[PDB]
Image (cartoon, rainbow, N blue to C red; front, side, top):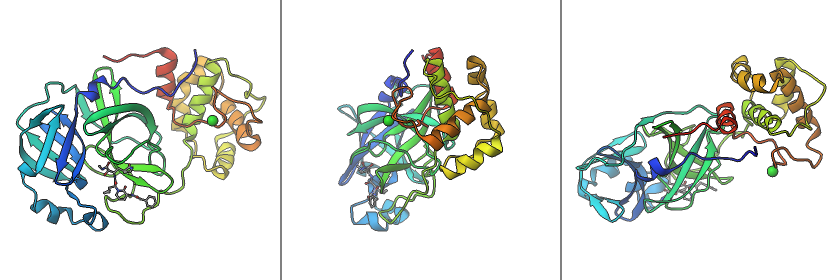
Length: 306
Ligand SMILES: *[C@](O)(C(=O)NC)[C@H](C[C@@H]1CCNC1=O)NC(=O)[C@H](CC1CC1)n1cccc(NC(=O)Cc2ccccc2)c1=O
Ligand SMILES: [Cl-]
């Protein structure tokens, strides 16, 4: 019992983090097999940032202009290429600590763990969600670029995020490991604004199920609703529309608790329309939307990784 925002154990990803320096700039790279992945703006001066021509800037960079350090040892860079907004530095040594891994591009609403790194060294681990507006609400300072977001599937690390930028409102933007930004963001110092930060409705419902599993039941009401009636209220509160796919995904939690998804939707509608009246749910004073239904099952069933 109890329910916490819980990250994956970071051990497997800690062994992949290195420091990448190009002229003036030091940030983090991910060393998998004989390739180091890092944000392509490692090549930019602060001047360059306003309007970079990365292809032009890259012409003036050779293998020896990329300093890659794994703890205290230099890796020899024997190749480089640009794929979208990431650099791939070929090194002459396969990372002996390369875990089983995949590159995945996650969907909005999906959660992952961030290992915040500075100078190739891990500083801390926390859980994030890809927001519907394709931002993340992270904790990133100057030096954190190239830090990665990941999920673990038993022994397989799925890398889904590389950190690139901060936006107004203190939210963050980055790419998958093929270097394609999530959302419309570009790696340039220009006026960019996120979009409406809508709530992940299916994740709020998953978290309400987690509360009932943990004996926190005060918000269950005597009402039911329809998808269409719920979505009419959802839209007003900037909630994502709930689909039958979402209902289906909550099936196991509904089964566990004996509360129909539509009954829980009616409970959520009353919390949206009436607020919490100074009460809390799993020690939160607002409706938490960074737990997926899988996240709740994992934590409430104690699924493990190795
Ligand atoms: C990254 O390059 C790094 O760590 N380098 C060593 C940083 C990480 C940033 C710094 C502070 N918090 C972070 O998460 N990324 C940047 O500095 C980017 C690089 C750009 C993408 C190529 N960056 C540079 C300049 C400007 C901005 N963004 C803003 O400042 C946007 C903004 C505008 C107005 C108000 C508030 C924010 C970058 O993100
Ligand atoms: Cl809160």
